[PDB]
Length: 61
Length: 66
Image (tube, rainbow over all chains, first blue to last red; front, side):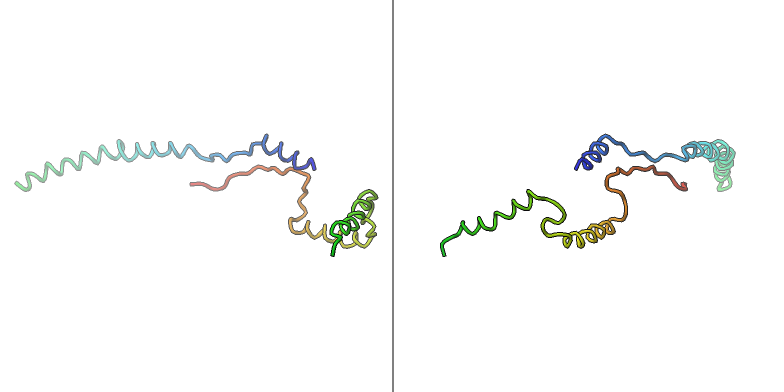
């Protein structure tokens, strides 16, 4: 006896650890590559794309 | 027969006697012990040699991620 009581109090009083990030810079590494997708690549690309449409109009016509 | 309870008396007596003279295997003598000692070890084997008067606690970590 008294062992269970020891373990009991210690268990109820106790908290176990937690597990934690190695990486929440990945979260951000996105928005940077997302800048890559849009502005950097988007804009120059967008301009080309648009032009072809208008182009196609006249070359249909 | 007729004695119902007078028999139970006869049985009863020795139960108290042994308890009020506790020591070894109780009037049994060593013979109970010799079995007991093995049996107690065997049960330890079923749970391994982990102490039962200790409280366990450890930490736990992390691995590769994506």
